[PDB]
Each structure stands twice: as structure tokens, then as C-alpha cells.
Amino acid sequence: MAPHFKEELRNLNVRYQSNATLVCKVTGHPKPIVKWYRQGKEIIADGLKYRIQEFKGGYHQLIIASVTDDDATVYQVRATNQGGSVSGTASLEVEVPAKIHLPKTLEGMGAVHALRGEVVSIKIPFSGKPDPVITWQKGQDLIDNNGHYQVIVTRSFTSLVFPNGVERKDAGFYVVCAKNRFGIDQKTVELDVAD
Amino acid sequence: MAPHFKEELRNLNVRYQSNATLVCKVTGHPKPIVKWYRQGKEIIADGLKYRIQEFKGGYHQLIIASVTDDDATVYQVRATNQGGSVSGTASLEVEVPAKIHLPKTLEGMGAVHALRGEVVSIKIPFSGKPDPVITWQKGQDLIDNNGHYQVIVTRSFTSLVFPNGVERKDAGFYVVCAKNRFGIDQKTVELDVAD
Amino acid sequence: MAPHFKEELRNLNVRYQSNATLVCKVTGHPKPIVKWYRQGKEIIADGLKYRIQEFKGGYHQLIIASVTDDDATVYQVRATNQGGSVSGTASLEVEVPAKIHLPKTLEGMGAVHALRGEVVSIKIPFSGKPDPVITWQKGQDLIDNNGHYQVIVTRSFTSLVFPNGVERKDAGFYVVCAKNRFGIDQKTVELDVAD
Amino acid sequence: MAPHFKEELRNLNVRYQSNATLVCKVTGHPKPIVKWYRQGKEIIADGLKYRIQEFKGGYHQLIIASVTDDDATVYQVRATNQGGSVSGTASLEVEVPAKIHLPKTLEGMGAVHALRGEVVSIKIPFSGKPDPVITWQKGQDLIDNNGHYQVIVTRSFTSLVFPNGVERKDAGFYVVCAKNRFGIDQKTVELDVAD
């Protein structure tokens, strides 16, 4: 009589830009009415980002289109009739391969044109969920923070900074790499220094 | 010496969610510096939505990721050196197949549950570029505006309205169809009327 | 000295048509040489279906493009130097949402036009991994095998058969539904019977 | 009475991996029966690669999924009733951006390890429709055929060959580039030569 989840919502791991479909099977008499929520705020289907669907035998599903990290959160489904109300919950995690995104390239590489003494930042956006490990190299030498370079890593970009001002010797090829469980990506940036 | 477009920008027609790439070839001495614009506002590449790329021999390209109708506009590319500045222009049109988007479905169809006398609207979002022709039917009878139904069509949705209040006879299966040059889509909505 | 997997291959579950990337980290001196295998047969990278990539610090990855159920199997990675050889193994499972594929539709539905006494099969291809549960209904009545209908389900299609020959009463709307953990899909076929 | 194409098939240009939809509108009494053909061989819809669809008012469409260059050809639609038969024809051209596909990479670049005197080929698959212009460079020097290098370009790959046997001086970074109207792509291959 009161609503029950005969098949409960499953936690999902979905690749970025795929559709995530959350499915459950509800029993109860009278037939329970189902509502869907993202972090406790009701989802009203719009036909585009969110589609809500029902099938004979008590099957309910929510399709979330083209998932991004913004969709990676907890969802609830609620089933109600005059006999009671109950919810179930699932998390969606969205897998985003580690990726370096060069805004501008010259010959397949980043290019920074600096003048001597200029405090240069080589700012490189990246993606990745799980958050990727970021590394920088000049040629075949790993860069970390020392007296010469500063590395900045935020949620969305990494910058290699020359806080003391660039020197002529700073010219060269810098390699930035992002790694997580879904892949490794690297790109090169050429820095040249003019007087 | 002054900049010239040896290969000018081409007008593009790109399918929705594909990447649009605008390419040109620039000559001039000194090597011209190129800037890109959307409707006369400079595009600053971010690595995601917009990537700007350059190749030996004067080739310049802008990649616009995952195009939507918002990207369907006029773009300019400008080439400048100390000898002069000139631009070229291309339009991007984004092809979106006609598509009906049911927010909620029961057994593959829309469902509207109405009470007698209720002023019902069956509101159906749709997509399509070129803007699609919208038609409504009840069974095998085309509906237009008459003394009984009102059809609303906007840029993003169409509603079949029962402005006089639904009658029991209004129960049934309504078919909405969107057509343009890239395809036809239709969906059905079942209306039931309770006392 | 001998090769070791500092980071072993991970079992993967990838959505159909996405790229699967298998990644590992190898140590050893001299630097081990890595080969990749699908079910014990070496993968020779072609740049399209298969790309093999290596990065400083001993990282190795195989990218399998646009995965289909044919790619859902066991893979091996082998690392060899003069000190030894060792492999690691991962399974790729490819998630394919349950989906019904109507070859031909009239007004959004299948259509079968039969004559009385004709042994009709309504043959419906479907996809789904895990293999989906298939159900058939006429209106709101579940069909299984009885004295009247025969249901065939294979790896790739389901047919509703009328082995005794269709009767006039067999006319109507048949609903076929495929369900797995990644979604539910249904479609309708209208059967009409002529004398 | 006899069949007529009120709306004839349109020539299509579709991006690689998109769906191509060919649509027409047929008149005639009795209602004409429509068949579809690829290069004069009938298409039998399978629900996957090919879906054939019909809508009230005489609309007929063929959906070709996930188009490849193999689909880029001429199609016919035929409409027949007892009063006559007529066909219409459209070409599908499939746009494939120029793209270089490195089978194996080390640090983002191809890698060829050669011994002195070895007749090396650096074999690089590529895609592009229209067929792309291919160029090779060593550093900032364009390579064509001369007494030292041989360039091979086929429908699917390009090789830079060292027909005389590699010399130590052949070591270095070779850049291969593919260009067509839908974009430019380049990749680098490092060649090292051991005694």
C-alpha cells in the first residue's frame, strides 16, 4: 500500500557530455507519484537538460543530458501516495579526462613573447575530474617552486610564473602535463625573450 | 607589405554541437598580427569555447567548440602590420534538426490530466534552425485555431490551449510535429479529463 | 632494475562511443619497453581505433576510440627490459543503454500490414549492455508465450510472432520495451489486418 | 494521381559522425509507396545505420547514422503507385576536418629510432574530406622531394622516406601538416639516429 522502492536508485559514474539516466522501480497502492530533486531542490523537467519518464510497472527515470561537473552531486527521488512518502538517493560523479586547453597556439605550441625583466605568467587552463596532478618541465627538467619559478595551481588553471622577471635564459620550451585516472595530457609552450 | 587575405574566411554551416573552424591565410611583411571578433567584439581565446591557432605560411584559424544557435552570427578576422590593417568576415549558421522535447512522458507519450472546465495548455518545447513548421493534430485531424482550440507558437515552444475550458470530449491523443530541412520529429500527448 | 607496474592498469567501464583510456606507470632500468594486447593478441596502434602514448616518468596509455561491445574484453600491458618481463591486465566493459531500434516508422510507430492467416513476425532490433530485459504488451496487457503468441529474443532482436496465423482481432498496438541499469526504452508497433 | 515530389530531396553536406537526414514530400493517389536507394541499390532499414520514417501529409525521410566517407555518395528515393513511378536523387558529401593521426607518441610527438643507413619511413595516417594538402618540414624548412627525401602521399597516409639510408644529420624534428577547408592540423615526429 505505502510506497516502496522495489529497485532503488543506483550511484552513477558518467563520462562528461554523456546523458546520465537514473532509474528506479516503485510499488504502492494507490500508484505513487514521483518527484525528483537535485540536492534537495525539486527538478522540474524542461525536456532539454532534464527529462522525466515513467513506464508501466512502476518504472521511473530521470535523464540528465550532457553531464558536466555541475551535475555531479546528490539526487533524490521521492514516491508518495496517501499511505506514505519515502525517498531514495544516488550520487552522480562525472568523469572528465585530464586535459590541457591552450587558448592560443603557434605551430601546435603555446607561445609567450616576453621582454627582459617582465614578470611573465604562462597561464594554462585544464580540465579533469578527479582533479588532475599538474606538472611543469623545462625540456627534461621537472619544475617545482624554487627561487626562480613559481607554480600556481587552481581549480581551473595552472600558471608558471617568473616572479623575479624573465631573464634571457628563461627562453625555451615548457611542458605542462595533467594526469588523472582517465588519462594524461601534455602541451608545450615556447617562451622567447626579447631585449 | 600591407596585410592581405590570400585565402579569405568562408561562410560556414555547421551542425549543432560540432566545432566550427574558421580558417584564413594572411600575407604581409612584417608578418601581420591577427585578431578575431564575434559581431565586432574581440574574441579572447579561453582554450575551451574558443581556440585561436596559427601555422607557418600565414594560416590562422579559430575553433568554436560545440556550436549552438548563440554562435550563429557574423565573425571578423583582422590582420594588421605597420603597413595597414584589413578585415574579413564570415557568417556561421548553425543547423539544428527539428526536434520535439517532451519534458515528462508516461509510456512514451506526454500526459496531461485535466478536470472538466480547466483551461488546459499542452506546452511543448521544440528546437530547430531553420525555425521549424509546427503542426498539431488530434488523431488524424489537423488542428488549427478555430472556436475550440488555440495554438501558440513562440521561438522555443508551442502550446495547444483549450481556452474555453476542457470538455470530456477533449480527451484523446494529440500529435505535435516540427519540420524543417534537417528533419521531421513528432510526439504524442494523451489528455484525459476527469470530472 | 626489472620492470614493475608502480601504477597498475585499472578495470574500466566506459559508455558506448566514448574513448577508453588505459593508463599505467612503469618503473625499471633500463627503461622498459611496453606492448599492449587485446585478449593476448598484440595491439599495433593505427592512430584511429588505437593510439599508444608514452610520457616522461614511465607513464603509458592506450586510447581505444569510440568503444563498442567488440572492445569489451580483457587487455594486457607488458613491460620488458633485459632484467625481466611482466604484464598487467584490465577488463573493459562497455555500457550500452537499453534501446529499441525501429527500422521503419509511420507516425512515430512501427507499422505491420498483414493479411488474415499470415504468420506475422514483428521483428525489433535492440541494444543494451548489460543485456536488457525485453517485454511485450498489447495495449495494457503483458504478453508472454501462450497458445496465441510466440516471443523470440536473441542477442540482437526480439520478435513477436503470430505462429497460428494472424486473426482480425490481432490488429492493434503492440508495445515492446527494453530495460537495463542504464535506462528503459519502449516503442509501439501498429498491426493492421486486411482480409 | 501519379506520384510527384512536392518537396524534392536536397543535396546534403554533413559533418563526419553526424546523422544525415534526407527528407522529401510525396503526393499522389493512391498514396505512393516509397523506397530508398544508395547508388541504385535498395536500402533496407535496419534501425541502426538506416532508419526510414514516414509522416502524415506524405513526408518521407531516411536517417543515415553516424556518417562516414563511405556514406558520401548518391541516393535515390522512389515513389510508386498504380499511376506511375518516379525517383529523385540527392548527393551526400561528408565533411571530414583535416587531421593527422599519430599511432604512437612519446611526449606528444611521434618517435622514430633509427640506425645509420636504415631506409626509414615516417608513416603518418591522416583524414580529411576534401582531401587535404599535406606538407612536411624539418624545423622551419619545407621538405619536398629532392635528392635526399622522398614524400609519399596516398589516400590515407603520408610517409617521409629517407631512401638513401638515414644519416646522423637526419636526426631532428619533422613536422607534418594536413590542411583543408575545415581545418589545419599538424604533428611533430622526432627522429633520432644511433650508430
Image (cartoon, coloured by chain):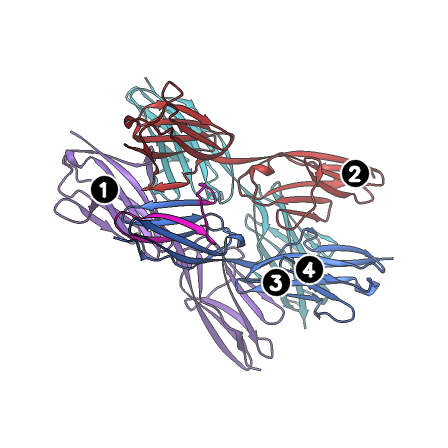
Chain colours: A purple, B cyan, C blue, D red
Please give the residue where the numbered disc 4 appears in the rendered image: C188
Within the image, what quadrant is residue B61 found in? top left
**Residues flagged by tags 3 and 4 on a common chain:** yes
- Quadrant assignment for the C terminus of chain D: top left
Tell me the magenta residue range: C23-50
> Is C108 placed above or below A163 here?
below
Name which residue type carries label 4: Thr
> To which chain does the residue with label 4 belong?
C
Looking at the image, can residue D187 be seen? yes
- The nearer-to-camera label among 3 and 4 is 3
Q: Nearer the viewer, residue A33 or A162?
A: A162
Task: Please state which of residues C165 and A106 is positioned toward the viewer in this rendering.
Answer: C165
Query: Pointer 3: what residue?
Result: C178
Q: Position of residue D90 (x, y in %)?
A: 66, 34
Check disc 2 and report the residue beneath it: D3
Q: What x and y, as percent, mark residue D18? A: 55, 43
Please name the amino acid that badge 3 sits on.
Answer: Ala
Name the side, left or right, on which C34 lies relative to A142: right
Callout 2 amino acid: Pro
Question: Disc 1 and disc 4: Cα gap in Å?
Answer: 62 Å
Instruction: Give x and y (percent) for residue D142.
Output: 35, 23
Q: Which residue is mark 1?
A: A140
